[PDB]
Image (cartoon, rainbow, N blue to C red; front, top):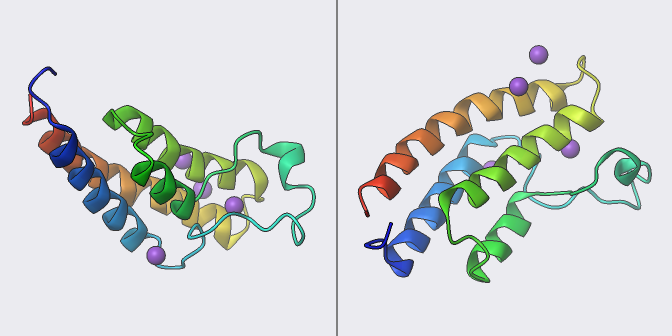
Length: 116
Ligand SMILES: [K+]
Ligand SMILES: [K+]
Ligand SMILES: [K+]
Ligand SMILES: [K+]
């Protein structure tokens, strides 16, 4: 709302991004999928996303609401489910990350709501 301040909001997103990365204990989503090694990746995936790209977007002031930040985290998970077969560790790690990251985002959303 009209009382929310830029700096406190961005510090909340920086802490939330660190918490979401802490849940990716495999470091699967740290960096963009390398297209030289996975050349069919963009056949399936229209908007690649990863935690490094999210950190760049955050520090470029591209996240000015909570839902745009959440949408990019959800894209990390949804892209992994789309590309990888259900029997893979990567697919099951993305399902887990959706669960654990959802809990991180619920606590962070309460802090955003208290900024008015
Ligand atoms: K990590
Ligand atoms: K992936
Ligand atoms: K599953
Ligand atoms: K899911």
